[PDB]
Image (cartoon, rainbow, N blue to C red):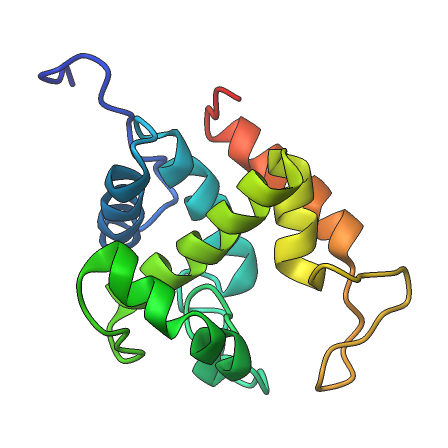
Length: 158
């Protein structure tokens, strides 16, 4: 279906339309021409399953991009400065805005998509065999591999 303008990135079929709108808004905030939306779609698929994959997880309450309470707290002032309003955890749009701010930070700071993803999953000090607060194995390398491949499969250009 032809768009005005022609550059409009097409939603992957498997990405729910509510999620697409969240990630497009985030993409707009970072001027990424729709490419970041594709990356964010891949991340959200892995983290939650667009919200469907959280039931029974001990970190279910962390929402769509699985930002831990202490991390959300650390980034409150920066979120407000970037987006113009206080972070509201009950808002799925905000959850995505917060996660995407953190992910953008990692990508910019470490200099690549792959490192952004690895560090988004494991933090800045990840090692093989590392463990999160709940005692779950953090497979940061596999995460980066999976999510990057998914981003590419979605038609990511970088």
